[PDB]
Image: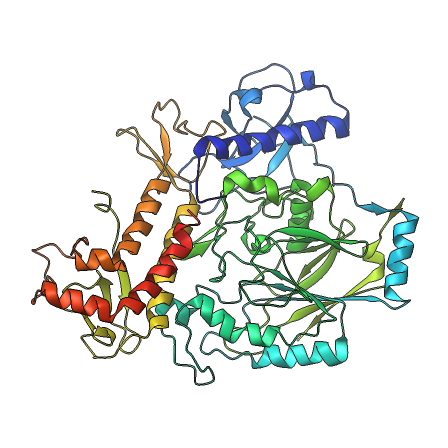
Length: 410
Length: 178
């Protein structure tokens, strides 16, 4: 896929989000379509309605509140019309721009919560093989996230120290590394203040060559016994696909060995033994700005609420329009392909990893382990963090949350 | 006509930080393409290839990111709103009753033209034939004081072929992907 943006196709995708949730709500609560009607027009009767949370003006203030939101209907539901929301009869809520929601009520009388997606399961045979793989011992997965060098130099000394540690002490089964590796917004890269490197015989002429001379030789030293997965950022200079969802990097081009490196898409979903991982590298946790009412909702932890919104929305970056950094960078959503950012198979992941510039964290929310490993190094050059996941050795629900320990390590 | 609305590639000097538009092997009061490369006229320091190409790539990516911000604009001259909101009927304007058509404000034609312009800057044949778009209008205070000769441009272009081609490959990274 090329750099095309097509408005009809983008709008198709946004329409389909509303329609597919309309079917999820109808099956879960066992309602008939005749119970759903157009909320944008007057009726005498209470109705059920599903739509997208949008601002009530298209040129809107940065800061929204419960009196300045509208609901957008699907093309079939209300000819795509948008209607202002009266939320005065509802004491507890958390909404955000792009959220798909279901109401009974346009004055909202009740919010029908979207149901949590199902968890993956495994057969007894599969779980026994996984048990044999590990030879009794526990599963270890390490997770890191860029940047890997500081803002004022090109030192990977900390990464070398880390690699030595995982090779010779920690000895995990898998290492997951999120970009950016060479961050295009790094201030020396941005300004072109790139120095001569005396430790390279031939100087790189491009940022792609800078990766081959700076990262490849150090990454190559990761033990072949540790499978290593690379997932990019749309800020990765080494990627030529700077929109989310983002195609995987090409391993051969990075000159990394086949023996232990796999390049994955952003986002990507995969299993390590039975455990389903959902990995996405746009900062939902930083970006999702809730409009909130109610003491009970506000007393909860923001990170719990945001993780539940993601699980309910069944997509790793449900905010729309996506956030902008003001022009320098952004979510860079390629709206036509938001489909690929939905939960694969409709399954909730066992472990969900969505790196953020917020402080590192690991939390169980709705039986899903949610992990932010934090940035590997801080801009100043001080120690950052990474995440270590240790899971006890195991149709059946994986209960990863009951068996997994997550440490956030300097 | 294709590049009439593109914007210039702005480079910053690694030593002294002076900013300037780069128009190819053409006259400028800010920079010179000498026999050993791109040179800053304020401080005389030479760009290395990585110092040039990292900036080319950074600009490209700024453009591509703006493009993916997905701003839209309305046709109707009596409305004109710009928004990132997209109606489930994409072309339809979100102003109550407005009949104008909505269009991505950074169209993919504009992006492609912007990249083709960047490509032209590092195109040897185009540099030699002097077919690049001028970076300066005649009344601009920075209009260049000295004009380069044709024969200087030919020579300087062949002397810098390698630099040009490497600068060009960085644009092509994104042009084949488009």
